[PDB]
Image (cartoon, coloured by chain):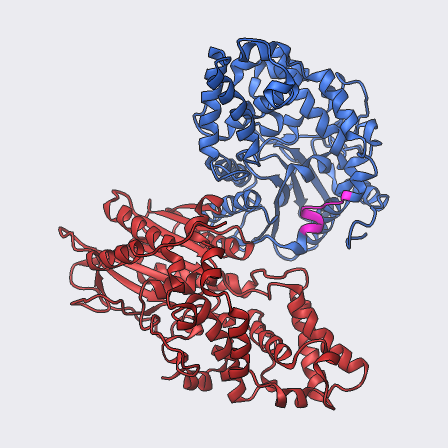
Chain colours: A blue, B red
Amino acid sequence: MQTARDEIIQDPALAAGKYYAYEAPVSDKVSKAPAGYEPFYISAFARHGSRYLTDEEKYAEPVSVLRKADREGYLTTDGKKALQVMERLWKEAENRYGELTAKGAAQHQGLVERMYKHYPQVFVKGAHVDARSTYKTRAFLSMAAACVRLAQLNSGLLITQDASAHDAYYIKYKNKTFEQQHLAQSDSVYRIADSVYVHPARLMKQLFTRNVSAEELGVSPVVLMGELFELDGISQSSYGQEGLSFLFTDDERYDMWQRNNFEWYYEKGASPLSDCCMYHLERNLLENFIMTADTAIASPYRCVTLRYGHDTNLAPLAALMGMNRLQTETTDWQQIADTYRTYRIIPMCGNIQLIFYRRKGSSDILVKPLLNEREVTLPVETDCAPFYHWADVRAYWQKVADSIVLPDSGMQHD
Amino acid sequence: QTARDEIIQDPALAAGKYYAYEAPVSDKVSKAPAGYEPFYISAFARHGSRYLTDEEKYAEPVSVLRKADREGYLTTDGKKALQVMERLWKEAENRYGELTAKGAAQHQGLVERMYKHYPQVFVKGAHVDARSTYKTRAFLSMAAACVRLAQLNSGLLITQDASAHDAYYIKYKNKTFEQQHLAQSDSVYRIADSVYVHPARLMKQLFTRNVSAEELGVSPVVLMGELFELDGISQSSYGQEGLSFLFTDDERYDMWQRNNFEWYYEKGASPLSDCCMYHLERNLLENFIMTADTAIASPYRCVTLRYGHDTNLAPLAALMGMNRLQTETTDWQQIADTYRTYRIIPMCGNIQLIFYRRKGSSDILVKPLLNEREVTLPVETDCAPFYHWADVRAYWQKVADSIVLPDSG
């Protein structure tokens, strides 16, 4: 539909991208399934909800730069206003770095609330909600919030939780060797990305009364601008905390989003600069979607599969599934945002949901794919969009998974 | 009963820190004085039943017996032990240190008995404030309990956290303090092994011939410790055979004593570590005091649930002054009289404080429970098993104020 540029002009919060605080779709409506079809299985992967920045230094470094300017008298009034905001953001996050916020828990309560409202026939008494997480507290506290909410919504669900190293091979897959096969020269690529997207000259004059250099700051202007942009976005993780929007023009807001958007496209998407197939990393997660759907479709019980993790794995999974046009390959720095937009893929509480439908007396299973609760296309033909035939989707995904070979990494192997 | 007789009646208790929690046999709870109703619960619970924390705790002993098997000096009893140990390792594979299904069921049972016995605490709109450490076994115990509470009363307000911000009281650690008082622990444990661990008979039961510690790769005392650990951890699984056929009644008691001593020494009242190692839990005691003050003054209704590790549960029990845990002795055999790990830190071990108020009276009462058994506190009371919170609080505050801990980490 709209350009990413127009979307971000209409809603500046979307430029936070990976830090965008999840919002339910404006429309509460759900596409009607073909006659006789009812939902019976839901399979999901959900990123943790809104969180603070992951390292104390992501607060401490830019704050100390501005406090020093203040102390030595070259911080402007806008600079002082910015410093005051960042001090409040840091105080909020103090000794809670990387951790889920109260707003982040509410996002996951809302996510399963809307699941329950939309597909009540899935969440019948005795149905086994199988929820799993990574070891990271932000991921499993998102699971914990969601599971307590489902238990409040229906006392009869059988809800189990785990956060086990035994599942890491698909719920938090990692292969540094594969990354190093493609990203060894990422330093060079990012220097080019910085010069294409990050334009710090105007902001430096807004922040400081006299001209400053990379050497007096302790960080380059490009780094300082990125750090201030990250703080502006992370303000969304808190209730009633203002950001730093007054530090960024609309074009700079768009460009700083583009800079992190490119990073995801490069490290985890279809960039030709990383040889187009970085999203092959999620073969195992894709296979776990296939196998657990196979089990639920053949099961005499009722099932729901919930997985809680990280955008590190969510972003490539959406591309590997073939959603929309995520697999489009381009090196045009400005064209990426056409088909690949992080706020539509990996916001806080970002999530993929597959809704499986069944009709009595018919072995023709249908599946509705949702990316952040919006219908998506899959690279197979269908006669009942937004619905797909599971037989066609399964064949395509299994063929994709079968074609991916991943290298030994440490003691881990295919 | 004595610890020796309790272990004769119920050998599973000798697993100590690995004993799989069981509810009290009677569903009865003591009657509060007239007009008193429970209104606040404050708890600290260890994670439920878990696998061993490191792969080497399975691999090392298993490889010893596989070596004996390959080279043909493993007895038939030895092969039987190897069979069960391979089974225990297979259960734990890639789940080292993790909560088991039984450990989750323990924590569901714990809150459902809180709910049954003190139902006036669990009313619509009450805030259940649950917090954990960052370790998955602790968090998942929390998560199992909170889902259970949600099912018992969806009107509760249940929040969950597992924050570095709570570590100073929910997972306290002070390596400097330990090195001040445990500096020669290596020497103390070599003596303790000599006192308690006697592997000659077991070595002859396991192997067809004498075997040197060099050929085993581990000393016979280490191997006996590892086999006893594997025997205990079988309790974490449903329907898993242990190794009871490798230990006589006397050895089972003595191996329990050896680990019991380790807790008494590192976390209890042993004169060998200068009698005040349980001072480590001053912050956790202060958190119990202040969250109780807040609940007593609150216009809302509250429950405080903390989920953690026996590293902190054991000293908390002693620092609160429960029963005779603070009794000081160097007599290796007398420890067990007043200090018994299966009564303090089993799997799902827990301290609960049940607070009661009477309408129109500011005299708050508190009932202290250790693994759901009433305990004494070093405070006078005119209505045991209940204590006046004003007296308990004054005693715990001065205990906390008397403690000096070094800045560490």
Tell me if residue A25 can be seen: no
| Residue at 81 percent of width and 22 percent of height | A330
Q: Is residue A287 above or below residue B2?
A: above
The picture places residue A178, in percent across and down from the top left corner, at: 80, 42
Answer whether residue B163 is magenta in the image.
Answer: no
Q: Which residues are magenta?
A: A168-176
Q: How many numbered discs sit on the rendered protein?
A: 0
Quarter holding the N terminus of chain A is: top right
Q: Is residue B116 left or right of residue A363?
A: left
Query: Would residue B317 be visible to someone looking at this image?
Result: yes
Q: Residue at x 70, y 74 (%)?
A: B62
Looking at this rendering, what residue extends furthest in the left direction? B360
Q: Report whether B27 appears left or right of A395.
A: left
Residue at image coords 17%, 64%: B33
Q: Is A170 in the magenta?
A: yes
Question: Vertical placement of A92 versus B306: above or below?
Answer: above
